[PDB]
Length: 144
Length: 144
Length: 142
Ligand SMILES: CC(C)(COP(=O)(O)OP(=O)(O)OC[C@H]1O[C@@H](n2cnc3c(N)ncnc32)[C@H](O)[C@@H]1OP(=O)(O)O)[C@@H](O)C(=O)NCCC(=O)NCCS
Ligand SMILES: CC(C)(COP(=O)(O)OP(=O)(O)OC[C@H]1O[C@@H](n2cnc3c(N)ncnc32)[C@H](O)[C@@H]1OP(=O)(O)O)[C@@H](O)C(=O)NCCC(=O)NCCS
Ligand SMILES: CC(C)(COP(=O)(O)OP(=O)(O)OC[C@H]1O[C@@H](n2cnc3c(N)ncnc32)[C@H](O)[C@@H]1OP(=O)(O)O)[C@@H](O)C(=O)NCCC(=O)NCCS
Ligand SMILES: CC(C)(COP(=O)(O)OP(=O)(O)OC[C@H]1O[C@@H](n2cnc3c(N)ncnc32)[C@H](O)[C@@H]1OP(=O)(O)O)[C@@H](O)C(=O)NCCC(=O)NCCS
Ligand SMILES: CC(C)(COP(=O)(O)OP(=O)(O)OC[C@H]1O[C@@H](n2cnc3c(N)ncnc32)[C@H](O)[C@@H]1OP(=O)(O)O)[C@@H](O)C(=O)NCCC(=O)NCCS
Ligand SMILES: CC(C)(COP(=O)(O)OP(=O)(O)OC[C@H]1O[C@@H](n2cnc3c(N)ncnc32)[C@H](O)[C@@H]1OP(=O)(O)O)[C@@H](O)C(=O)NCCC(=O)NCCS
Ligand SMILES: [Cl-]
Ligand SMILES: [Cl-]
Ligand SMILES: [Cl-]
Image (tube, rainbow over all chains, first blue to last red; front, side, top):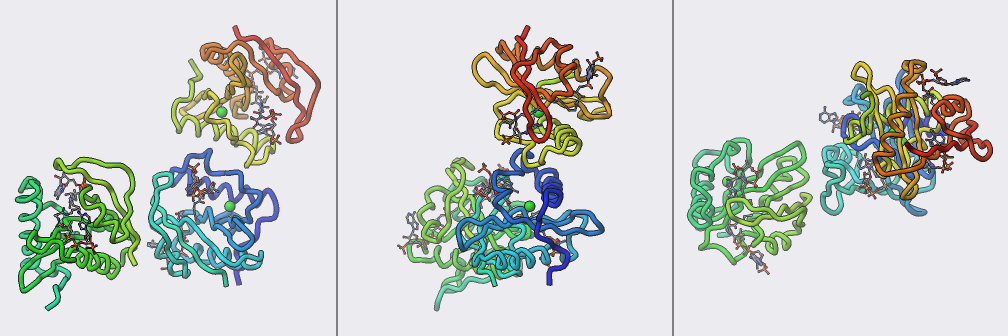
């Protein structure tokens, strides 16, 4: 099903997520480092993918109510992009969110990723908006 | 006949666009003639509208990345304004941009045209700015 | 000379780098707790060697007269050569320059002799935070 990805269940795995997120969002994309980790890590559910014992992909699922999750921090290390890992990650995210009892997902997608997310049957909603100098649009999907 | 909007795919059709642009932006709005035609004509995608065989409306779509276009040079000949032609033009622009594989549009709209563009579900972003003595504001929309 | 007041994002992230290496990786502070909501209001110091960040601390005002000294760290590679002492001298000087009069700190107990050599004094009793023994230490700024 989703064999390369695991639900984070200890601190080491969580810090592996943080490592990827710092490399991608902070170092590569210029998100201020102090903003990368927020007050929602504990309430969120995290996924991690490893390759050869090295953390290479992560996302988090943040419940906003009883039915709906926000998908956040979607990242694949640059070294491992373009080989289907992001797609596998997102498939694992959807499956995990459904397993955890949710029905709907929303995400503030970076605009460069729109075609990728459309291929996963997410749909744009609303209008574009800048956060941290990056263009985004909300995208949504029911979880199946 | 209906007005017909077509993707420019030869030099004569492009010249029809330039004709409208010179009449509207240069002669009517005072844009310096040497600035009307720029170095982005070939990379942009142009639309021409004909009515009774005469060029009456144009715009260009300028890709800025894989997902996003800048809408530029939006003009209807003065003779044909106030009868829905601008609306039809913009609908044809949006459709062409989507057909060409884009997802989002941005535009530096002249402020006098804000209500026109709001009627097409564009939304203002940022703040106003002067170019060529004319007030503008950025406006954006997802393409559907 | 060695230490500069942090005045841009790059310098601040250099502080964060040292703090992660020392407090998180070495001392086991949970990574999500390293950076807090007080980074903006605090004043930070950074020291470099070979063009690389090697020492940091922050000064966090708690009222008009008093600062908390926090995040005092020297990379393991550069310890035992007087850099921590220089850092703390720079912290005191900066805090005084910034208009403060007194400093308090929740010192890790292993550092008590280091801080006593800088004329800090213990107050109160010991307490555990993140599995590490601490004691409050204080000094007037001169
Ligand atoms: C509070 C929080 C939980 C939701 O914030 P929000 O305003 O409702 O949603 P946004 O998606 O627009 O997030 C923008 C905020 O997150 C912060 N942020 C942290 N990491 C970010 C990232 N990778 N990309 C963008 N913004 C990020 C920004 O600094 C901004 O905070 P601010 O409002 O204090 O300026 C936020 O901390 C967060 O996690 N944002 C999501 C960032 C993210 O993961 N983006 C990738 C989506 S796959
Ligand atoms: C978005 C991201 C997670 C995708 O991960 P990935 O491992 O490259 O993804 P995949 O290999 O599974 O490719 C998924 C799709 O992305 C697009 N894509 C990937 N590599 C691409 C490339 N070199 N050129 C163009 N599009 C590309 C394609 O649409 C691709 O689909 P396909 O394989 O069916 O053709 C990754 O690029 C990333 O982490 N980017 C930086 C962080 C970020 O922006 N995250 C999004 C926050 S909302
Ligand atoms: C380089 C270019 C591609 C983008 O420029 P930009 O600075 O990113 O965007 P702006 O929309 O603010 O354009 C202002 C520039 O375009 C030029 N320009 C050409 N035709 C113009 C027009 N109809 N209205 C305003 N500026 C025009 C101005 O002289 C100015 O050039 P400069 O910076 O060398 O002085 C520019 O040549 C262009 O095409 N601008 C868009 C003009 C336009 O079509 N306006 C109507 C939008 S519906
Ligand atoms: C701006 C322009 C393209 C609009 O085209 P148009 O043919 O006049 O507009 P339309 O007749 O299609 O109008 C579409 C709708 O917007 C409304 N609208 C158009 N211009 C408006 C204005 N200035 N104020 C308020 N509403 C306006 C119309 O009333 C119509 O709504 P309706 O169905 O209620 O009647 C045209 O006036 C033009 O070419 N102007 C000169 C060049 C220019 O300024 N271009 C814009 C560069 S960003
Ligand atoms: C909120 C804050 C500003 C003050 O907290 P405080 O309770 O008044 O003071 P303490 O010195 O006892 O700090 C303990 C708290 O800081 C957190 N913390 C962050 N980095 C730490 C570190 N290096 N050492 C110890 N605790 C640390 C702990 O998780 C604990 O948080 P909690 O109460 O939510 O569990 C705190 O975020 C902080 O910065 N603490 C100082 C940590 C530090 O720099 N220690 C070295 C002193 S030289
Ligand atoms: C504590 C720390 C900042 C000191 O920096 P440093 O570069 O090693 O310190 P210096 O070389 O300037 O001086 C070391 C001093 O430690 C003192 N010291 C430490 N343990 C001592 C002990 N058991 N007996 C006597 N002196 C002791 C001495 O006074 C020594 O000074 P000296 O050179 O005059 O003999 C550094 O070891 C560090 O970063 N440790 C890990 C992070 C940490 O625990 N920070 C404190 C949070 S409150
Ligand atoms: Cl995560
Ligand atoms: Cl054109
Ligand atoms: Cl610091």
